[PDB]
Amino acid sequence: MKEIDELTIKEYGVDSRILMERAGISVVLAMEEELGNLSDYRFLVLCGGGNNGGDGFVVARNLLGVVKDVLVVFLGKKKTPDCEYNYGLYKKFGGKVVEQFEPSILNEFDVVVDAIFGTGLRGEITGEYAEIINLVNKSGKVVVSVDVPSGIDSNTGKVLRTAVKADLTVTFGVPKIGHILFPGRDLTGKLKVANIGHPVHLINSINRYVITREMVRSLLPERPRDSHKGTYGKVLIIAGSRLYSGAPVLSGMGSLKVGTGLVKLAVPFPQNLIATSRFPELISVPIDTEKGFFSLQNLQECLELSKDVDVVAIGPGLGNNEHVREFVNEFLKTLEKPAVIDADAINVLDTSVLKERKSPAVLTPHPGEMARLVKKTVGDVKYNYELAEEFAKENDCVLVLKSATTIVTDGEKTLFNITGNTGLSKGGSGDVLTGMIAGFIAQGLSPLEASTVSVYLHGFAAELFEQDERGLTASELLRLIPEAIRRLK
Amino acid sequence: MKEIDELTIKEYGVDSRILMERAGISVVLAMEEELGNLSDYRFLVLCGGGNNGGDGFVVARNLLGVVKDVLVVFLGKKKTPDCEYNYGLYKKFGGKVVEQFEPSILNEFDVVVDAIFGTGLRGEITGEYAEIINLVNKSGKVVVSVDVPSGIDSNTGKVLRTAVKADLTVTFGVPKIGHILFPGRDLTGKLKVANIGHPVHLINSINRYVITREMVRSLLPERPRDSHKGTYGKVLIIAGSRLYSGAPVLSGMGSLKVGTGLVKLAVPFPQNLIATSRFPELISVPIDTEKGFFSLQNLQECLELSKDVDVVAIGPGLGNNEHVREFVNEFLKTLEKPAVIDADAINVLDTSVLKERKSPAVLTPHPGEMARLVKKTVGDVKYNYELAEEFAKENDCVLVLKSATTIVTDGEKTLFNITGNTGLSKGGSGDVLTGMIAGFIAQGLSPLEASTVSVYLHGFAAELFEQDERGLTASELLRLIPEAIRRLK
Amino acid sequence: MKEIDELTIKEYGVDSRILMERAGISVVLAMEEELGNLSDYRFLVLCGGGNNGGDGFVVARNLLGVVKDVLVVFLGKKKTPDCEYNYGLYKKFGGKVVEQFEPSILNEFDVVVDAIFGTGLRGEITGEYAEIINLVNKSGKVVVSVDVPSGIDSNTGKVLRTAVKADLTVTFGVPKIGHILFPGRDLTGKLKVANIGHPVHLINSINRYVITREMVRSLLPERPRDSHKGTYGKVLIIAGSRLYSGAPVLSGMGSLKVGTGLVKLAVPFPQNLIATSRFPELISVPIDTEKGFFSLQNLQECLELSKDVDVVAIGPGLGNNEHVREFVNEFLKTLEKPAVIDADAINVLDTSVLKERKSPAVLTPHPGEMARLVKKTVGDVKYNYELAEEFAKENDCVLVLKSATTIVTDGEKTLFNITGNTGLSKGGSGDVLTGMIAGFIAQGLSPLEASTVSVYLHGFAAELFEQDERGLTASELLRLIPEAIRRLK
Amino acid sequence: AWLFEA
Amino acid sequence: AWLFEA
Amino acid sequence: AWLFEA
Amino acid sequence: AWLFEA
Ligand SMILES: Nc1ncnc2c1ncn2[C@@H]1O[C@H](COP(=O)(O)OP(=O)(O)OC[C@H]2O[C@@H](O)[C@H](O)[C@@H]2O)[C@@H](O)[C@H]1O
Ligand SMILES: Nc1ncnc2c1ncn2[C@@H]1O[C@H](COP(=O)(O)OP(=O)(O)OC[C@H]2O[C@@H](O)[C@H](O)[C@@H]2O)[C@@H](O)[C@H]1O
Ligand SMILES: Nc1ncnc2c1ncn2[C@@H]1O[C@H](COP(=O)(O)OP(=O)(O)OC[C@H]2O[C@@H](O)[C@H](O)[C@@H]2O)[C@@H](O)[C@H]1O
Ligand SMILES: [K+]
Ligand SMILES: [K+]
Ligand SMILES: [K+]
Ligand SMILES: [Mg+2]
Ligand SMILES: [Mg+2]
Ligand SMILES: [Mg+2]
């Protein structure tokens, strides 16, 4: 986006002041849409010395004469050319600026416009900057942040010591990564993305997107009337153990609820009988195991079962011991079908196997599993989209890094999912998503497309739960999937 | 219908021109009912040299003076007497015909009336015929086909190289097989069947019908108040294996949900316990098997269980190995009760057994199973109603050939089912239908009647699913059956 | 219309049988629209030997097999070619005809289709024809007349000894004069006009029309926003006497309520004060008279008042004595403005004056006044549109012959009004209409257009009265005019 | 409208 | 119903 | 109100 | 839609 601004100015020829005017008015319009008529509010505009602050001066100048009171607190030392120009206008228009504030200044105002720092934030916020931000955050006033809440790193979503908590953030051109990843996503409040006059071709060229309803809608496969179950693919799910008998059922139904034609589970006996007692639509093949866990002794039966399917999902509830590790790795090395690799199949995965596979793969770790997989800490991998991209590229796979915002990447293209809620923060929800991805691959979507549609629909289904989200369970999530699909179209 | 037209003209004495006038006006009325007031639309009428085209000229002439613009593109070489007569009228009325067109001609029109070919279609469409049809299909205009969309073979539903895709098709007297079978059914769009003056006795004599709501309504058996479960019959379902424990449950509930009094499953132990854990209404008899599959060692127990029932369904989830084959064939040879034969019981069936049975049978193959049963390709049997009729007649059975349009035949009478959607394109839906048919036979319907009611209700239940059809599962289908029944009356 | 049928057959080339088929089916469709589903009704079709009867045979044949029972009673001696052809079809279709009836035959039927006589009626109906018509009329069955109720002369609306009273009449191409004029209009019941395939150019060429809402809508003058009262014309009303002080007020407000800019009354003093006490918007000029009636002594003042107006209405409440006669005739001879001549100005009118006037005139007699004006009986002039046309042509005027159906003619073009009800059968309603016509002329409509719009709106306003029509008074009628105008657009 | 006028 | 079946 | 008056 | 995406 910095390149996008520079190109719009230097090559397309749009005066930087015009972009800044457009930025500022878009904030006024956004606030009006959120607050209704602005004429009865008193506005405190906090302006840094950069172009964020310059945007803020445009906001302030445009409210002059139209609202009850505007005051700018200018907190910078020096001003960029466009900030200075717009400060100049604010003042010729009759605007009041002050360069100091008392903790009490919030008293006589209703709305705080936060134009202190935008994408130009570098390093931790301290001193007067920090103290005014902590005062704003304690004030209970309505907070509207210009571009990004001040103190969020717009490339990562991290808080640089302290940050503004906004009710409304108005950003320009495109959402920034820091509105999408937490904690930044939380501090952004309601996000409006304003068109400020960039050529649409530049905006559309951005390589890291939010997954939207329209994107998912156009990816959902067709259901031609003259069809039969074979039209809609077959999935094999290799899952479960004597310890974890539930996982296979949740994964299997996840595939069925997204429209897959036939779903087969391979589960150790007698735990396989659990699935069909709950959902008799499922086929649940009993696997004879020595001690209740898959081992090399089941390799041949599983490859056999794989010949007649379009995709194999593996891992939920397998357990993690050496015999499972030997089985999972020899299987994936020999399987020449797309594989969805989850849970304990990730925990025992030899990543050398992924490189040598000619067939595709999607991996679906939560951060704990990703951390163990690449031998880093949870903190180093969580929301680390560049690490996810590198891993995907080096291992020729699609990586689905699960979290409140889920990252979906194949190393070239990266998508961010923002549907869902905390009802998915409960055992089983991951097992459902695994089935969904396998299901969509079986119906003919690419591994990346399948992952994109599934993470969106999985979160949206959770949002459709009628009671308090914390009581949502995986079984209820399954029931909500076809409603999510209907709402998508 | 060709005989029906000829008889109406040559024996009843209706002038062929009167039939043609009635055809054309019925198209105008149909379009008005679909589009509202026609006076603001511009119409492009594409007329072949046959009687389809003659119908088209009646349409065009009748729109003259009443709509914004009509143009006929006459694409034929020569004209039949009635086409020529009606061309003559169109022109005396002030109509414009042209015999050439530019790809751009679709520009100045809103509605295309497709009167190029009807039932007179012979062989593949090529040349100007093909190119105008491909232009119409790319145009996004409203398309109204006269009789059958041009390019559909009206006896089979097949596309002869290319065909018109219509929003509305108006057909005369009776629907043609090509509006009922796919792909033709898809290209027909909304079908209206117009009465153009044939004696009703001739229309009613047609021997191949669409299954309608009224037909199914009058077949539903009575529920006299002074009744008990024995009034409503008993079904035995012989089904399942260690691999396929779910099928029996879906078939059994299918029988119960259509109003059967008592339903018993015979399923290998311990897979039998699966059914009553889900639905404790079911009786699920444990069969001791050597390896988890029915074999000759269970012949005697199954015949015993059969003595106390009115019908036996056999096949869902049995598996297909030689011991199952030996059991299924010896059983059916000895069973003197109506049999509903499905799935793996079809895969192992010796058709000589069917001929020697004195008791009736219904077979319920999908095209893959029918293909294997008669040693032909899926493509040769799919929608091949004449093959289905021959098979039914030669084997003294009712054949239910499942597909988006299902064919139900006893060799004399053939019915086509058009209820349902792609939510049934998923494992388990067939198992439900098997139970439904057995259930209705048990309540006293003939095998043909039972099959007719069941295919209709099974599809209609699917349509009543509240969310996106692709998320429908067999268990949900079962829950919807009694609502389908209520809506039918 | 007889010429229109002949031309459609002989020059356009439409087979007479096709027209007859179209006639008959249009009756079936009309009945369905009126009665709902026809399948539970029993139909008695009464067919004469002419083409009306032939239409009836088409009706009967088309109901065969679809309704509960059809019977034709054929009452003719011989059959025209098309009647014979369609009788032939009815019988090949399995139809029952009988040629005799018992008074009791109406017993077993619900609907009577009256196809005995249409436009071919000549002379009084007697014998079996009369007796079946009197039986139908006593039967309380639903009656549907083909073309015109049998026994109505379709050129005059007169009853030829006896006639069918229909609930529904379906006529072909255009309404006939006998559906429009009483008593025929009463016996027609609900009239549907069916398109049976005549070229629209022929239908549109008919020279005597019903005034419709669409015609009146497109005649209503424009109200451009930049306007003032002069835009909308000025009317002078010369009216009233010491005996009839109310008439001027009703005429004056009639002009104002249709949108006239300025209205002036000339009324003998002190009766002029009556108008402004009721409606102070009116200007009511006091005329000094010897005995309370206009006379030659007021000629000069009235011509003076006329110079500044666009139209003059004269006559309501003037009284009829020799001094009024002398005044009215000398005035109209000298007045060079359009004149609306009503009431007592008609009673004293010397028609030689009309011929010598260069300016236009509209005359608005009820039949009593028309009778006195042309020295004939009320019975000779009532509904006599040809007499009205001759009078209009010979006297170079527009004639508005008031009655339940009002005739508006200029001698070339003749329009029939069918709006209104019996609330207008009460003193004063005529005085309102006079003002309305003058008003519309003042706003720039031709005398014929003005008369056309006014008779429609005047009747429609009466229909908008909220309580029982018999309690409608002229003052209430005035209040309803602007609502009539709003509903028209 | 095509078939009937009222 | 007289003219059309659906 | 900020952008347009009617 | 022209000014804002949500
Ligand atoms: N607050 C939240 N907001 C949105 N989405 C969320 C949230 N919390 C969780 N989710 C989503 O829920 C799903 C959880 O998946 P997992 O982390 O795999 O959780 P779980 O279902 O418990 O895993 C089951 C089992 O498999 C193995 O990982 C491990 O053995 C675990 O016990 C992911 O899609 C994740 O993005
Ligand atoms: N698009 C569709 N539209 C309408 N109806 C459909 C559609 N797709 C399927 N159906 C209907 O769904 C039912 C499917 O029956 P089956 O083909 O027997 O499918 P299924 O339930 O998967 O069979 C279960 C098992 O038994 C054996 O055939 C085989 O071992 C299979 O796995 C049939 O009634 C069919 O007409
Ligand atoms: N049943 C009816 N249906 C429809 N319209 C009707 C009906 N009855 C009357 N009308 C209409 O009402 C109006 C009556 O006009 P007039 O006959 O002139 O009656 P009226 O208002 O009583 O005349 C007032 C006075 O002026 C002189 O004619 C005479 O001195 C009379 O007393 C006409 O437009 C007529 O068409
Ligand atoms: K900011
Ligand atoms: K066609
Ligand atoms: K008649
Ligand atoms: Mg998990
Ligand atoms: Mg099946
Ligand atoms: Mg009058």
Image: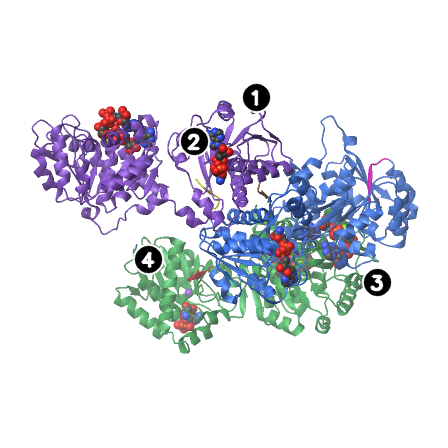
Chain colours: A green, B blue, C purple, D yellow, E brown, F cyan, G red
Tag in front: 3 or 2: 2
Q: Secondary structure at mark 1?
A: helix
Image coordinates for residue B408, horizontal then vertical, percent: 74, 46
Share a chain, discs 3 and 2?
no
- Residue located farthest toward the bottom when viewing the structure as drawn: A11
Q: Where B305 falls versus A353 (above or below)? A: above
* Tag nearer the camera, 1 or 3: 1
**In this view, the mark in front (4 or 1):** 1
The secondary element bearing badge 2 is classed as loop
Residue contact at pointers 1 and 3, CB within 8 angstroms? no
Q: Foreground mark, 4 or 2?
A: 2
Is ligand 1 closer than 8 angstroms to the Cβ of mark 3? Answer: no
According to the picture, the residue beneath numbered tag 3 turns out to be A297
CB atoms of marks 4 and 2 within 8 Å: no
- C74 lies left or right of B340: left
Distance from label 1 to label 3 (Cα)? 95 Å
Closer to us: A38 or C226: C226
The answer to whether marks 4 and 3 sit on the same chain is no
The residue beneath circle 2 is C152
Q: Position of residue C376 (x, y in %)?
A: 26, 29
Marks 4, 2 in one chain: no
